[PDB]
Image (spheres, coloured by chain):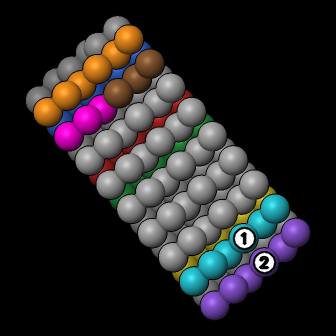
Chain colours: A cyan, B purple, E yellow, H green, I red, M blue, Q brown, R orange
Amino acid sequence: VQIINK
Amino acid sequence: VQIINK
Amino acid sequence: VQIINK
Amino acid sequence: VQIINK
Amino acid sequence: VQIINK
Amino acid sequence: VQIINK
Amino acid sequence: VQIINK
Amino acid sequence: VQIINK
Amino acid sequence: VQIINK
Amino acid sequence: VQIINK
Amino acid sequence: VQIINK
Amino acid sequence: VQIINK
Amino acid sequence: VQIINK
Amino acid sequence: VQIINK
Amino acid sequence: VQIINK
Amino acid sequence: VQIINK
Amino acid sequence: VQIINK
Amino acid sequence: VQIINK
């Protein structure tokens, strides 16, 4: 699982 | 799973 | 699991 | 912005 | 911003 | 910011 | 900032 | 800042 | 700052 | 598990 | 600063 | 487990 | 500063 | 386990 | 400063 | 276990 | 175990 | 065990 905010 | 916000 | 905020 | 409920 | 509830 | 509840 | 409850 | 409860 | 309760 | 805030 | 309760 | 704030 | 209770 | 604040 | 109770 | 604040 | 504050 | 404050 990958949850990313940039 | 990939949830991405850029 | 990877939760990332940059 | 990421608001997540699972 | 990341607000997460699992 | 990261607010996490698991 | 990281606020975590597991 | 890191506030953690496990 | 690190406030930890385990 | 990796929780990262930069 | 490190405040730890285990 | 890796919890990182930079 | 380090305040520790184990 | 690695909890890091820099 | 180090205040420790074990 | 490694808890680090720099 | 390693608890470090620098 | 290593508890260090510098």
Residue at 73% x, 82% y: name it.
B3
Q: Which residue is mark 1?
A: A4
Examine the image and state in which quarter residue E4 appears. Answer: bottom right
- Specify the amino acid type for callout 1: Ile
Considering every residue shown, the one lying at the far right of the view is B6
Instruction: Return the chain for callout 2.
Output: B
Q: Are marks 1 and 2 in contact (CB under 8 Å)?
A: yes
Which SS type dominates the magenta stretch?
strand
Q: Which residue is mark 2?
A: B4
Residue at 30% x, 32% y: name it.
Q3
Q: For the image shown, how many numbered marks are present on the structure?
A: 2
* Disc 1 element: strand
Percent across and percent down for residue I4 are 39, 42
Q: Quadrant of the C terminus of chain E?
A: bottom right
- Specify the amino acid type for callout 2: Ile
Residue neighbourhood size for the residue with mark 2, other residues' Cα within 10 Å, grouped as few (<14), some (14–19), many (≥20):
few
Write down the region rendered in magenta.
Answer: Q1-3
